[PDB]
Image (cartoon, rainbow over all chains, first blue to last red; front, side):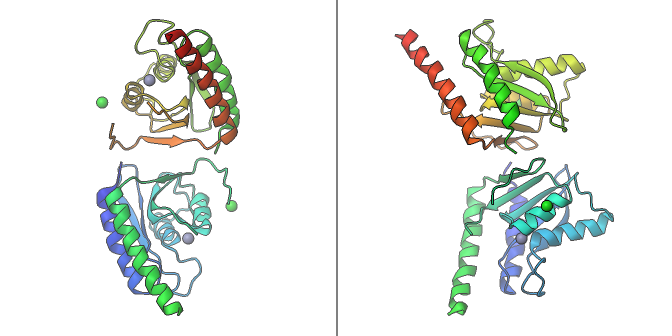
Length: 144
Length: 144
Ligand SMILES: [Cl-]
Ligand SMILES: [Cl-]
Ligand SMILES: [Zn+2]
Ligand SMILES: [Zn+2]
């Protein structure tokens, strides 16, 4: 569909990540009934851990809850197209679908049982783009 | 992935439909192991039946094989983006994924558990576009 309520929630969460120095990305994992089982934000720089993107964080939350590395029954929704580290972690726990809102400007993948699917929600996409733009502006100001 | 072998097969089949007066569309339904369970071509005008597009034909083949209207365990691959009649029939048998090669130039859908996903296979897409173009050229020649 367009996940308007889940996206409202994720966009609200990611603000937290932006306040603390990380690209404001939030994401959740859902079961087939679209219930959220785990939610996480990006905390790579905040916790000085190369792996702590929102996607790997949410994967680890669910591994913890279910005591299992097999998430084949679940789908992932993120505000921003995942990097390749996260894409590979998502693949390695057998999640078959990644919904993302905003693709990443910054590989050639012929994987399957793994679809990367852009959510169409223009209002939410424009809102999240404005949040990211504010983050990057502050990024270049501190860069200089 | 890019379904290169299945697409080779479908593009070969659809030629049959083009020879007999129908837009040359072919499609199959696959299980989770990507095995084909049913394959069909468009035969609307050939059999004077508004419903006999390739997608509805393949659905009926599988309903027949399984004696069930519940195809929730299966995915559909077609050469051409489905019309809305077929999209609704696919939804009504609970198939969750439609892979298509070529989108249709000729609605606003907020359905979910139903993803419409364009296959990326440039060589196969260009080949199928050339086949369709030949079909339409002959169409306008007979039109006049
Ligand atoms: Cl890998
Ligand atoms: Cl309906
Ligand atoms: Zn990442
Ligand atoms: Zn149709």
